[PDB]
Image 1 (cartoon, rainbow over the protein chains, first blue to last red):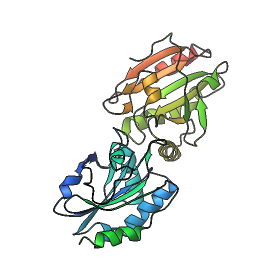
Image 2 (image 1 turned 180 degrees about the horizontal axis):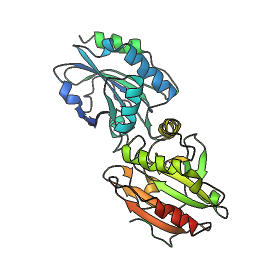
Image 3 (image 1 turned 135 degrees about the vertical axis):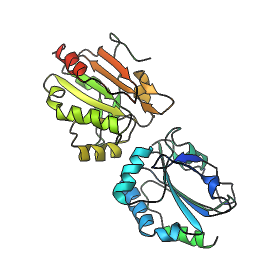
Length: 153
Length: 153
C-alpha cells in the first residue's frame, strides 16, 4: 500500500522536537525533501539509520535538499533522543492521531502501531520521485537516497 | 469518567520497560496495587512525580504493595527513561492500542492523546479503594497514596 512514484506527497503539519509546526508544503518551490519514516526512538536499527543520516548531513540538508524524520513518538521523546544523539534535522511526531501520516503514505504497520522503514523523496512541485518501504528488521541503503536527490538538483 | 471507589478494576496486560508482560490480575490475593497513570516520559512534572515515587519506593513496593506506572510510551522510551532516572519499578506501555487501558479507567485525555494524572489503589480482591484524576498541569499529593495503601495492609 506504499504510495508510489508520481503520486502527490500527502501534505502534513506535524510538531518537531521543539514543538514547532513543520509543514511539507512549506518546502515547495525551494527544496527537494527526504522523508525518513522509522519505527521508534531509542531502538538499535533506528539509531543506526539516523546516526548515518546525521553523519552525512551535508548530503541531505543543503541548498537543494531537506531531510525530515517521522515516527509515532511525541516531541519530548524526540527532543531527548535528538539532543543525546546530536540530531539537528527535524524529527516529527506522527503521535496523535497515531500513525496518521504514516498511514497516508502507506507505510504504517497496523499490527505493531509503528511506521515501517518508509523513505520518500519529494520534488519541488510536491511529487514523490523516490519511494521504498523496508520492514522494521531491515536496514535501508542510503545510497539510493543520495542517488535520488542528485537527480532533482 | 474516572472509575470510582467500589468499581472492579478493569484487567489489563501490558509490556514493561524490559518488554515483559505485567497483568493486574497477577497481584490478586497477594498485593494491593498502586496504579500511577501519567502523561509522558521525559517531561517535567512526570519526572518530578516518578522521582518522588523512586525516592520513597519502599513505601509503595514491599510485601503488601506493588506500584505500576502507566503511560502511552512504548517500552524502549520507558527503558531509557528508567535507566537514566534510576527507576526500578515497572513502567507499563499503554501504547497500541493507544491509551486503551487509560480509557478503560476513564483517565485518558482524548484531545491530547495522553493519560491524565489518574491514580488508583486496587485491593487484593480487585476492587478500586482509592481513585483520583488530576490534569496534566497539576501535581498529585502522594500522601494520599501512602495513606490509601496503609488502610489496606
